Image (spheres, rainbow, N blue to C red):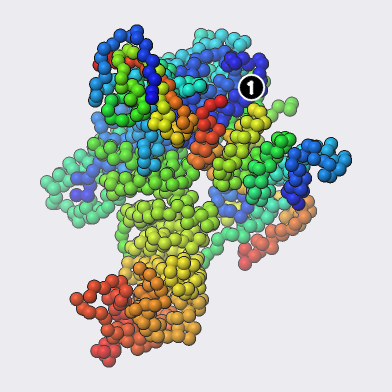
Amino acid sequence: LVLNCIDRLNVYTTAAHFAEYAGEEAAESWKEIVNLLSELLASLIRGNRANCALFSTNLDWVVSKLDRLEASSGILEVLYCVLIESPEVLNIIQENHIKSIISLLDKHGRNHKVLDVLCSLCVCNGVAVRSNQDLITENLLPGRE
Amino acid sequence: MDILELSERLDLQRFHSHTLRLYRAVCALGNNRVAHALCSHVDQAQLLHALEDAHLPGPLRAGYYDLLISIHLESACRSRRSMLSEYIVPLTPETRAITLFPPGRKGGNARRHGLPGVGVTTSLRPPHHFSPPCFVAALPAAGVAEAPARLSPAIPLEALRDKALRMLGEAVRDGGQHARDPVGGSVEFQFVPVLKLVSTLLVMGIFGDEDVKQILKMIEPEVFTEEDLEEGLLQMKLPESVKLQMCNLLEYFCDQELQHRVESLAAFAERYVDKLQANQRSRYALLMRAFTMSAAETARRTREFRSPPQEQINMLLHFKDEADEEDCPLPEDIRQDLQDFHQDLLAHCGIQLEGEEKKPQSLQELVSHMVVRWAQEDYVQSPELVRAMFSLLHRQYDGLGELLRALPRAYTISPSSVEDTMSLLECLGQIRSLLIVQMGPQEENLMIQSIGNIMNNKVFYQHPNLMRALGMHETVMEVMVNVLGGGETKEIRFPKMVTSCCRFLCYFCRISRQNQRSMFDHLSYLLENSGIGLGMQGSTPLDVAAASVIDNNELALALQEQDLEKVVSYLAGCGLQSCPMLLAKGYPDIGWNPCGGERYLDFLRFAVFVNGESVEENANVVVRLLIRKPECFGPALRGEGGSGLLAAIEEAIRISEDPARDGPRVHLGHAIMSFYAALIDLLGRCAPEMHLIQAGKGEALRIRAILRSLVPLDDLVGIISLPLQIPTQPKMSASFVPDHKASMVLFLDRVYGIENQDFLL
Amino acid sequence: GVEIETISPGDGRTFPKKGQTCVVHYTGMLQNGKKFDSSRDRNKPFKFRIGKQEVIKGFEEGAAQMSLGQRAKLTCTPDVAYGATGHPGVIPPNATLIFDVELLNLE
Amino acid sequence: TPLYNLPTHRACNMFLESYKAAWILTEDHSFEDRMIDDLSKAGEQEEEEKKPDPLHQLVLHFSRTALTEKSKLDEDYLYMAYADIMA
Amino acid sequence: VLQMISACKGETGAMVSSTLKLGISILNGGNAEVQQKMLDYLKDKKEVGFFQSIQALMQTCSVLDLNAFERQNKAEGLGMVNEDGTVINRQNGEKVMADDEFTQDLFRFLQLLCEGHNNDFQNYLRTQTGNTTTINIIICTVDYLL
């Protein structure tokens, strides 16, 4: 129901000046409620081991809902908790997620959290992954600039 | 923007530190390709300039040091550390020329123990095999083509070692001068990275003798002069990480000392066994010269000839003292040498031998006093430092325990037989380095190629103690259980690699006996894992289980019972299954498992007869388990559901010639007849021994009655009386197998018995 | 269609034969970009043979018509040097390569 | 005949096994009491709420490993050896 | 020691053997101070599971059996001579019990734990009050004796 609520609140094409669809007293209470919901999910999946494994079912939706203009705060931290506290979802990561992460890094400035997430995305719990490392070294650094 | 700018642009400095962290994480645990890629960006000159510079900030200095460590001196260090617990000595005059070497110059037994790691140590470890980086070489056109991965980029080792030595000298000089400006802004950023670098270089084994002597001198210039100014690191207040680095350094030095000690003991052992062989030859010659005028000639002949060499060696050695008891067939010449060597070895360890601030004048006393001094300081808030400290303290008080742990991993290799040993060790190191990495196509191809290039080694044939030690069978089992289990239906992923593995398992079973038992319990775990997952075709581990118990006569007697229950339950489940792969392969849907049932019957055939006998306990247990479930051995066609065995074999025959139920190399009739032959052979081999034990007990009679009542008469004779093919147009495995008649004869002889009329018929 | 800008000072009238070994002292330089390789940084000349492939064909054909001690700017076209795939993680795809080879072999 | 005319490797291995099954590991050290006495005797080389320097950091470390999460623990031969030494 | 013995549950590995040996070593003679400290710690913490772990550990103890003895006798009968396999076929004939030392150590530790006549540990062991679960070790010990 939380995911459904987030999806229903995220039907806005820009979530900035589309408040006329809902009406008044909604435009001001948009960024704060989005950040509060993201932080609620964040504190929910933080600390628990089984919860991260249970929630690690649809990472594509989280990846797609990452660079949602204002959604830089939060959301990303949820993925970081999932990666740290559940090192088993790191098996179905295709090039689309890496491209989305690189686009987020180039679009939202030089944020250290993005580099931390990319750092945690290669090495697993004592086992290295050749595919993820090779994908990272050719997409994030295909050259320079 | 200038690197040296730390006061401003703090966010940029944090970003660069995290970028270095990402670079180090990418180049972690192998991946020589990204190693070369990073060598393209952060080249050799930049790394050396960042090394030599001292005005750099702390975090960036630590990041650059750890990046250089993880790029250049990482893979070789891991490979050499993975085999630091293995000690192998060859037979060269250099080995005979090295011993404990007491300081006899104005000394003797009551002298120093010598500086550890001064060289002249001999062992068998593979070379690092570096390669210079390059970027003007065109990539091969063929994709991979079983490429042997790559090699880490090479850097000048001597120049790097000299730079590290001068860096540590400058650091200790600055620490002695008590300057208020650290290199990295703190003591940690000044001491930890250089200590980590010098520890990695020391583990590398690049230093010679003068370098190690200088390092030991500058560590503590108080009790290392047997070979106020410049105070050592041991007399300086330092944080926790410096303590960890020094603890690792001391652990490496102690490991080197232990390796030297065990090599010296191996040389002494070779000399002692040579002397013992010479004395035994002389004693045999004198006995041959004078063999008369005696009464215990037969006893002496049985003792020195009709006895295993282990027992003879144990008698001639363990009776040398027996706590001052003698009673040994050896003179009193080598006994004095043995006692002197034992006393010298006990003096070398931490035993006073007399009674059981002060200058230590040694290493063990020095490290013990230093650890006590560190304990006497404030409470340590780092649990890992405390654990390493206590491990180092305990490791330096019980030499007997570490010696007893290290002796099973010691062996002596024949001279001029080191090339094969190096090849085997390099292959094992490659196996481990691919074990620490997740599986995939290229790495499985490399593993298959390596395990196919290890067969022709001329080492695995002999010396079972090499593989009994080390634990490489455990490594193979970990690899295979990683590729097989852990992912439910992921067992079918990556096939065609278990064939070489299973061949290796069977060979390791057939080598020796203790290895046979160990791999027996391990293969029991494997058959459980295969049963939880239905197994696989081809080189099934069930075939390995059948081939492992071909001739033991010891494991089957003490074999468990729940494993048989699991096996028969899996067989019943396969019999009640509909074989989804067979129907998709082009065969009609039949609720029976031909291949699985045949393999299970073949395995059960090899786990009953042992060595031609019949264990009554396992026989009755398997009979009770098999007959407890009526839904077994084909309940719908064997006769349980209301059919007949003769009708079943006639239907199988009618299917066999001109089949129509199936389409395209294994059909149903051959599988049916093979299954029936295997079941009847298993029943015949399960008969309660012979008439020698059936005349005294009633359990054998009851088993015989049940077996006779299970299958009716006038059936085996009718099957035998069925005509065969033309006796020698070409035929293949579709018609009657001549070995079926042998099974019929064996079952008739071992169950029904004999009479006149049936015998003549 | 490869342009060569020979620098006349540096003398040398010994053309490289086919089958022998000669050393180079080049430094890499990407087009409209940065420096990625430098033999001077490693302080070690690169040794390679002539006529046995093992290098870029474009680089070989650019360095063929050169004398001893005569540096130039060998611009390698990307369609034959590294192709549309390129080196995965160092050289971006379809990019020209610029080098300044310096000869110091004593033969 | 089985004694002589044998490769030196079998003799060396057999000697190693026999020396392993010999007067070694016969409790001829008695070093545990000496070490235990030598540790706790150093209470303060140069020193109310301060914890004792020896025999207390080890106990606290073992207790904190006891009170950790993630079900039970294994291996840890250090606690093995130390408990055996004290006993 | 009480925390180490309360961590491992059911498993009879070397962990439990070493903990029980240390408990024998420290409680030999029955010091009143140690018993008082353990009672105070158990009353303060009020942690359940230690009694459950003890009950599970003692429930899986070993007893003599006839089929195992027959198997051991058949193994000791040999019938063939292998490469010094006599000393490795059996662990000096301990295949029948393999747990007598551990069971004796555990029962000795329980005896040393409850040897004082304070009439305090007996009531706690029969029915503990600080926890919401009763174990009643006496009945389980009676079952083991039976």
- Which residue extends farthest bottom? B757
Q: Is residue A20 above or below residue B337?
A: below
Specify the quadrant that holds the N terminus of chain B: top right
Give the image location of residue B721, x and y in percent.
28, 86
Position in image of residue B161 (x %, y %): 42, 19
Residue closest to the eye, E72 or B435: B435
The chain letter for the residue carrying disc 1 is B
Name which residue type carries label 1: Leu
Q: Considering the numbered disc 1 on the image, is that residue within a helix, a strand or a loop? A: helix
Residue A125 point in image, percent of width and height? 56, 41
Q: Crowding near pointer 1: few (<14 within 10 Å), some, many (20+)?
A: few
Between D65 and B434, the residue placed more toward the observer is: B434
Task: Determine the residue positioned at 24% across, 21% down.
Answer: C17
Confirm whether residue A75 shows in the render.
Answer: yes
Determine which quarter of the picture holds residue B227: top left
Image coordinates of residue B469 in percent, x first then y, are: 38, 45
As displayed, is residue A10 above or below residue C53? below
Between residues E23 and B656, which one lies in front from this camera angle?
B656
> In the shown orientation, is residue B242 left or right of residue B604?
right
For mark 1, what is the residue?
B12
Quarter of the view holding residue B348: top left
